[PDB]
RNA sequence: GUAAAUUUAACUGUUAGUCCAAAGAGGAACAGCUCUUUGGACACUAGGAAAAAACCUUGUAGAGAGAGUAAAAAAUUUAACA
RNA sequence: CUGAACUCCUCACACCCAAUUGGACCAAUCUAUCACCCUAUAGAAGAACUAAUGUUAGUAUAAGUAACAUGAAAACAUUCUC
RNA sequence: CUCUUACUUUUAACCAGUGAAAUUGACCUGCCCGUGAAGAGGCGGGCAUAACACAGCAAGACGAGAAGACCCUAUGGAGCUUU
RNA sequence: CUCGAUGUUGGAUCAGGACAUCCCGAUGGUGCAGCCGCUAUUAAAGGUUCGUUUGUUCAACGAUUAAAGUCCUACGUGAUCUGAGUUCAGACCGGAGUAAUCCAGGUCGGUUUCUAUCUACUUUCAAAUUCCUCCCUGUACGAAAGGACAAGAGAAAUAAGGCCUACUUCACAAAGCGCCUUCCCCCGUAAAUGAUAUCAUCUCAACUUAGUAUUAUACCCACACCCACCCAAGAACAGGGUUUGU
């Protein structure tokens, strides 16, 4: 009835052995999935208007500046795809939703810290457990066989993506920091009233309206940034350079999807469909893909002639 | 009030009155005082009334006990085992006669709220109503919107 | 602000006896193998720790008598020697603290 | 908000915090084992590790001598640091101290820890020991290990 | 067949269902026509809910109500059915549904002019 | 909305009361009784 | 047709009034306003008018797992033209 | 058709108005005489408390809340910090 | 101040010890409209609705506190002034 | 209704609501050429400035703006704040009175308590409004003067939501003064075909178009390792990591 953990009863000799054993199994399992197209892939249909393909899960490496050919400076966020695989596929009818969904998980984690039901799910899948699992709505033609890895080249420079992540958590906060309230004067007689809400309602109603802005927990919630341009792709390290900043702290997992904004509808005609298969790819992609307007690091210094 | 007290259903003792009527009062125990104004009416009841009352009720054994007491009492016991004690303190001879006659006529069941003013073990002769009592039957017992011989 | 009405014992029992207010059962208690007294898994046994502290204090009191004053920390290593023992080869050049008792079985000479 | 704030708020402010930690560190150098509130020992442990590194620079390094002069309030301990403690750890690159939680303090139920410099002459603490290799689970794993090593050599 | 209910008069345009989310500005008013296209069972459900007694049994009674917008009924629901209730409204026949016997039985009431273009 | 000023059934502005069908029939029923009373008091 | 009335004897409390209908006065043919007058109701019960002192029905007191009633529900839909 | 405490039905009947007024009973206490497991007839009177921001005492609620306290290590010798 | 931000101490929050005060008819203590001694958590019509802590907030409970000090009244007082 | 108390102006803070609309949208009429206007219908999503004197709400004035709307909410809101004014006890001036003392007068000064028991509420998860610039164009219009609309492109402000590469306050981090993202709709009328009424008639006639969204999709979605440790998670609790438990 007392709780236990994985190495509680292990001896000095067995702890290193177990760590090495489980570590090697994880690496071997990841290496066995590197050839999706030689392992009975599902049908690869052509892209059609109205088709929605799967997205990725990436990690927020940090922020970096790049310069366009006109000389403007744009700061970008580095998003690295780490151990991203398709986990589960649910048909349109069974999802209970308008479209079929594809579950994707990224970032490998320790098996010792996962639940039994989760562990046995990954055992039949033949993959190590993932820190985060996200559900992507897709069309029938875009279905991918579970266990297929996904890379950063799935996204190509010049397209727009939507990034969703949990924001930085600031805990319980006052109305000034949380809601941008003006507060009260510092001097001129103010008595213990500088950062207080003030009046929260009118006298007649005799109650506080639901949804009233009050002190409370701030941050640590899911937010989406829409219409972020993909400036550059690094195929060697699988890092998607995206315009602007994304929600959440660096080293957090983010959900990357094709942009939903109406202006960017039906721009996937030239994008990999259903995804990018590096093994299938006839000609290996260059280590860096650049948008036409980006100043590449080795390009000559800008001249306005 | 009804919610603040117990209740029972109307009933009888051993189906009394069905085959024959049996008086349920079984014993009466009087406790009078030779001296004492409280028992004046009880002493006069023992002189002229108790003897004639016993002649009419040969199935009730009456025990008259004369002893010093401030409150004379009559204790009635019934065949079902119920025991009832009623004070006759300062009651007139006529008042006591009425009380004693009432005790003779009671069954001995608890004098509490009776849920229904009637009782029956055979409430239905033609069959108690059920949801199908007045529903017609259909050919082959087919349900609404049911394809037969598919 | 003052209470508008007395709070009933019924309301108070709900607050006071909420499972959040109750003491939680500890599942990390175990028997110390050395001494048999109870201990928590992540905490040193109180019985064994006290035993070590009592011997540590006796040695420190002896160190005091040898130093015989404040600001007299030695510039050499120290060894504790018990009745019936003599300095080893690796105990030469070290301050010797002598204890008038037999070496405790749990205090292995190193 | 205290994201990435690595130091605790102690004592009466920043200066008092250093002085509180310095007294703890001075006691440790003299006695080589002390007990104090868990949080304070955890804070002081980092300084106790770095002090040895300064001691390893030697008594001729003027910067090391100034550091030791500040942190050791009892000047007889400065020779001990350079000539006793630092030579003892000559062959180690770190891990000079061990910190263990002890039962809560009686008076105020404060969480408590014992800290000591490894290699001292004091009676050894009842250190936690991992299960024997001869236990049922460990023997079953030894079999699995033996089996995996034999299959690799083949 | 709750999707095929019929209102008399202009109730499709005039009858309004009012709700409030509870937030400031949360008052919502939709016509029966708008509600019907959004939720094909809401109208019948709301009519029943308002007719049931306003007590704690009401929501229990609602669990025994099974509304389906079309003829499709789950097989389990179909197997337990006992009796179908007669439709309260008699559906009037369209002019194209009358048999020639019925048309012939109704007399011609007037004689149109032979030279009228019609 | 739809408030009646002050108290409902008094004062200048009042809640309108309408005459139902059965209220009319009730009055006519008693008018018939009194009409007959007139007759039997005439002789 | 009815059963009260006056007188004798001995006393207390009430003497800060509300709405409704009606006849008027004041105000502004305002007031849930103010002032008199005739009557009613209320300040006592029950039913009704949605909740309801003042509108309507109805009063004399208990029990009943009977019955006949009183007052008692709001109706209405519209512009052609020589 | 439904629908009152109106009316009828079986049995019973002093048993639904503030101030005020008339009347019938009565708890406990003491005294006279009875009674003698707690009474009777009378004579008396500090003779009856859901309410006076009542008086005294007990214990609740607010509440285990507001608030309050001991510089550090150590051999308890001593030393250190301020 | 535009327009606020960061840090330290206090308080704070959690653990341990000790342990008050005003307040309190009873409470099994929702929202909207309407009603009403005329501004309803408690009435009518609707809607909402498993139970139970901790931390915040100050719109309401015509919140607590002081038998309103303003105003009027009492054949109620007192101070001062005076032809 | 309230005097065994329902705290009295203006401001600060945060605002909820009505539309009888100040700006932005859509329309009919004009003594509407155009640009500006006037007037009415429809529209309450969004917005509706900063200063000088004054206690002021107002008012006047300065500079702007697409516009600086009207009202209700205990003349919203003091258990959130402010106390210049009004309206106690002191004092002066003019005036009244024999005096005490007084006057809608002016003037200087003058203590704003509460530890939250109950109700309510504490991330409406996420579609954006507006000005200006270039261009159309010196075109349509007009005697001339003057001078657009629609589409197209760019750049800003505000609002909402995020972030730290640089700059700045700063420095394992939090921030703005910095940077990044931001997507539907408005129903007033204007027109055909065509009856009652064999023309005509946009029709509370049957009907046809401008003319309409099941507002869209998006977000969220597994769970007895869990004693302990760490944490960009956090008041506690919860949450993430430990394959980083000498
Ligand atoms: K009225
Ligand atoms: K009525
Ligand atoms: K700062
Ligand atoms: K409040
Ligand atoms: K008052
Ligand atoms: K001023
Ligand atoms: K309450
Ligand atoms: K016409
Ligand atoms: Mg945080
Ligand atoms: Mg400020
Ligand atoms: Mg103050
Ligand atoms: Mg202040
Ligand atoms: Mg009213
Ligand atoms: Mg009089
Ligand atoms: Mg009046
Ligand atoms: Mg009836
Ligand atoms: Mg009667
Ligand atoms: Mg009677
Ligand atoms: Mg008696
Ligand atoms: Mg007596
Ligand atoms: Mg008395
Ligand atoms: Mg009492
Ligand atoms: Mg009292
Ligand atoms: Mg409290
Ligand atoms: Mg405190
Ligand atoms: Mg202190
Ligand atoms: Mg607090
Ligand atoms: Mg405490
Ligand atoms: Mg009170
Ligand atoms: Mg109300
Ligand atoms: Mg609370
Ligand atoms: Mg507060
Ligand atoms: Mg109340
Ligand atoms: Mg109050
Ligand atoms: Mg008073
Ligand atoms: Mg006098
Ligand atoms: Mg009061
Ligand atoms: Mg507003
Ligand atoms: Mg309008
Ligand atoms: Mg106000
Ligand atoms: Mg205050
Ligand atoms: Mg207030
Ligand atoms: Mg002032
Ligand atoms: Mg003067
Ligand atoms: Mg002043
Ligand atoms: Mg243009
Ligand atoms: Mg035409
Ligand atoms: Mg025609
Ligand atoms: Zn032990």
Image: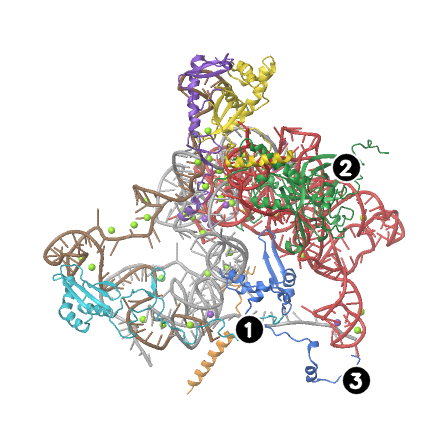
Chain colours: A green, B cyan, C purple, D yellow, E blue, F orange, H brown, J red
Q: Is mark 1 within 8 Å of ligand 16?
A: no
Q: Find disc 3 in the rendering and name its residue.
A: E114
Q: Position of residue D15 (x, y in %)?
A: 54, 23
Whether residue A172 is visible, yes or no, is no
In this view, the mark in front (3 or 2):
2
Q: Quadrant of residue C25?
A: top left
- Callout 2: chain: A
Q: Quadrant of the N terminus of chain B?
A: bottom left
Q: Position of residue E78 (x, y in %)?
A: 58, 66
- Callout 3: chain: E
The residue shown at (25%, 72%) is B22
In this view, the mark in front (1 or 3):
1
Mark 3 vs mark 2, CA separation in Å: 90 Å
Q: Find disc 2 in the rendering and name its residue.
A: A288
Question: Dot 3: what SS?
Answer: loop
Badge 3: how crowded within 10 Å, few (<14), some, or many (20+)?
A: few
Whether the residues at callouts 1 and 2 have beta carbons within 8 Å, the answer is no
Q: Find disc 1 in the rendering and name its residue.
A: B141
Badge 1: how crowded within 10 Å, few (<14), some, or many (20+)?
A: few
Left or right for B12, reference A212? left
Q: Position of residue D141 (x, y in %)?
A: 55, 36
Mark 1 vs mark 3, CA separation in Å: 60 Å
- Callout 1: chain: B
């Amino acid at each position: 009835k007392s709780g236990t953990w994985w190495d509680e009863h292990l001896s000095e000799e067995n702890v290193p052995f177990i760590k090495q054993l489980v570590s090697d199994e994880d690496k071997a399992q990841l290496a066995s999935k590197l050839c999706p197209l030689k392992d009975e892939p599902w049908p690869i249909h052509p892209w059609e208007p109205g088709s929605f393909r799967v997205g990725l899960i990436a990690l927020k490496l940090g922020m970096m500046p790049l310069w366009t050919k006109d000389g403007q400076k744009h700061v970008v966020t580095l998003l690295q795809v780490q151990d991203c695989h398709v986990l589960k596929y649910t048909s349109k009818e069974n999802c209970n939703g308008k479209m079929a969904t594809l579950s994707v998980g990224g970032k490998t984690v320790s098996r010792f810290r996962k639940a039994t039901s989760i562990l046995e799910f990954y055992r039949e899948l033949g993959l190590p457990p993932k820190q985060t699992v996200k559900i992507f709505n897709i069309t029938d033609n875009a279905a991918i066989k579970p266990g297929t890895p996904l890379y950063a080249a799935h996204f190509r420079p010049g397209q727009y993506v939507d990034v969703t992540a949990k924001t930085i958590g600031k805990g319980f906060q006052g109305v000034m920091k949380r809601w941008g309230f003006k507060g009260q004067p510092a001097t001129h007689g103010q008595t213990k009233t500088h950062r207080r809400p003030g009046a929260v309602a009118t006298g007649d109603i005799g109650r506080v309206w639901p949804g009233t802005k009050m002190p409370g927990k701030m941050g640590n919630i899911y937010r989406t940034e829409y219409g972020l341009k993909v400036w550059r792709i690094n195929t060697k390290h699988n890092i998607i350079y995206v315009n602007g900043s994304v929600p959440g702290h660096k080293n957090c997992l983010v959900k990357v999807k094709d942009s939903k904004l109406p202006a960017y509808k039906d721009l996937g005609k030239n994008l990999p469909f259903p995804t990018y298969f590096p093994d299938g790819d006839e000609e290996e992609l260059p280590e860096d893909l650049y948008d036409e307007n980006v100043c590449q690091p080795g390009a000559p210094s800008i001249t306005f002639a | 009030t009804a919610r603040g007290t117990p209740s029972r259903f109307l009933a009888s003792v051993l189906h009394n009155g069905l085959g024959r009527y049996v008086q349920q009062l079984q014993r009466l125990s009087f406790s009078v005082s030779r001296d004492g104004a409280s028992s004046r009416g009880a002493r006069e009841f023992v002189e002229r009334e108790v003897i004639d009352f016993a002649r009419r009720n040969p199935g009730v054994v009456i025990y008259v006990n004369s002893r010093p007491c401030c409150v004379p009492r009559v204790v009635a016991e019934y065949l079902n085992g119920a025991v009832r004690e009623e004070s006759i303190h300062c009651k007139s001879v006529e008042e006591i006669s009425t009380l004693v006659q009432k005790l003779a006529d009671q069954s001995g069941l608890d004098v509490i709220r009776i849920r229904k003013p009637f009782h029956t073990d055979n409430p239905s002769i033609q069959g108690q109503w059920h949801p199908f009592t007045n529903k017609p039957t259909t050919f082959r017992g087919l349900r609404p919107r049911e394809v037969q011989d598919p | 602000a003052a209470p508008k009405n007395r709070r009933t014992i019924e309301v108070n029992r709900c607050r006071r006896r909420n499972p959040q207010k109750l003491i939680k059962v500890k599942n990390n208690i175990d028997v110390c193998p050395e001494c048999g007294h109870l201990k928590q898994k992540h905490v040193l046994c109180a019985y064994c720790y006290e035993k070590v502290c009592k011997e540590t204090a006796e040695i420190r009191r002896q160190i005091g008598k040898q130093e015989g004053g404040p600001f007299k920390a030695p510039t050499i290593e120290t060894v504790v020697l018990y009745t019936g023992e003599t300095p080893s080869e690796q105990d030469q050049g070290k301050r010797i603290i002598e204890r008038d008792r037999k070496r405790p079985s749990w205090f292995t000479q190193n | 908000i205290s994201h990435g704030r690595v130091f605790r708020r102690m004592g009466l402010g920043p200066e008092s915090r250093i002085h509180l930690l310095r007294n703890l560190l001075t006691g440790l150098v003299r006695h080589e084992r002390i007990e104090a509130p868990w949080a304070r020992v955890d804070e002081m442990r980092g300084y106790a590790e770095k002090l040895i590194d300064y001691g390893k620079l030697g008594d001729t390094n003027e910067r090391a001598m100034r550091m030791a002069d500040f942190w050791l309030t009892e000047k007889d301990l400065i020779p001990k640091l350079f000539q006793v403690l630092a030579p003892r750890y000559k062959d180690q690159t770190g891990g000079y101290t061990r910190m263990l939680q002890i039962p809560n303090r009686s008076l105020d139920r404060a969480k408590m820890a014992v800290i000591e410099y490894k290699g001292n002459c004091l009676p050894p603490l009842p250190l936690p020991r991992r299960d024997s290799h001869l236990t049922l689970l460990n023997q079953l794993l030894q079999g699995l290990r033996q089996d995996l090593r034999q299959s690799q050599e083949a | 067949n709750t999707r095929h209910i019929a209102f008399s008069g202009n109730k499709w345009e005039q009858k309004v269902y009012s709700s409030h989310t509870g937030y400031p500005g949360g008052f919502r008013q939709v016509t029966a026509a708008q509600l019907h296209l959004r939720d094909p069972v809401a109208i019948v459900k709301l009519a029943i809910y308002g007719m049931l007694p306003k007590n704690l049994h009401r929501r229990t009674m609602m669990e025994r109500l099974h509304l389906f917008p079309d003829e499709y009924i789950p097989e389990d629901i179909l197997k337990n059915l006992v009796e179908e209730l007669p439709q309260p409204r008699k559906i009037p026949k369209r002019l194209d549904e009358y048999t020639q016997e019925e048309i012939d039985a109704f007399p011609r009431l007037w004689t149109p002019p032979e030279d009228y273009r019609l | 909305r739809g408030r009646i000023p002050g108290r409902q059934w008094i004062g200048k502005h009042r809640r309108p009361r309408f005459v139902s069908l059965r209220a009319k029939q009730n009055m006519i029923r008693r008018l018939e009784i009194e009409a007959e009373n007139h007759y039997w008091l005439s002789m």
